[PDB]
Length: 36
Length: 259
Ligand SMILES: N=C(N)c1ccc(C[C@@H](NC(=O)CNS(=O)(=O)c2ccc3ccccc3c2)C(=O)N2CCCCC2)cc1
Image (cartoon, rainbow over the protein chains, first blue to last red):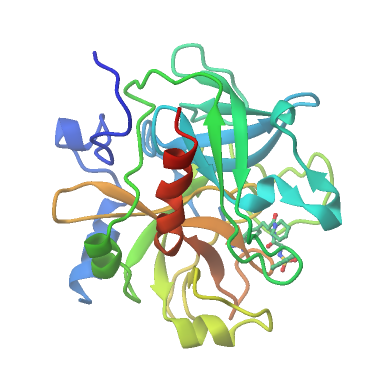
């Protein structure tokens, strides 16, 4: 446990930090590589 | 959120909801950017035509939720606000330009599994992710459809809603509205033709548009729900505060009035 200001971010605990992917995640990724 | 799904638990940890204290009422969503700074749209707080001008003592921030109805002992941190900051150049009397606001809590929150920061955007990630056709994600607990205002409106999500919407290119955004559109907003949602639907609606204002980067596998807030004509009308797009073109500001206040 530690405290601080805004630090690492944007990785959700129960997803990225567990290396799991959520239901809809795959649409965004498929749009990306369908553009540039 | 019009055509969203039920969200997976702990899906958007950054999801804050603004309540008015007494009488209890969901007002807006917001994002947890830090353990004491919640981002929101300016208009949840100040829209003088509908006599809305919300004082610091009028509001309360519920963080860690999933159900809209239920108080959930185990997940949920209710803070209260020390300061409400709204942009000098928030232009309500025309076109909701620079519709952003930033709320300092009274008390830092202890992050948990379920309460955790958004990244704000950087030069490279804005420039890399904000292209037309790229899908981002809007969330919140607001109207599942466009509604005539009755008090018990019936259309209210049980569980937080998620949708994924394409960014649309500026000529097309400009072309869809008589209202003067400016450089610090962007729009998103499907074209007519594209098989698929989605929007935010009333009570999803203030909440994140986030995109996830394939660089380093983190999520960033590209937009804030700001406005639109209706919810999910053909030929109309949802309009979002461009967080990055107000990032130069986004830093400045937390670092002016700092301690
Ligand atoms: N993406 C969506 N479909 C969407 C997005 C946001 C909302 C909530 C939002 N309501 C509206 O935008 C209602 N549509 S509105 O009536 O077209 C509207 C009203 C006033 C305006 C003033 C300045 C600039 C644009 C304006 C747009 C709100 O509470 N506001 C506070 C009052 C001013 C307007 C915004 C609803 C729908």
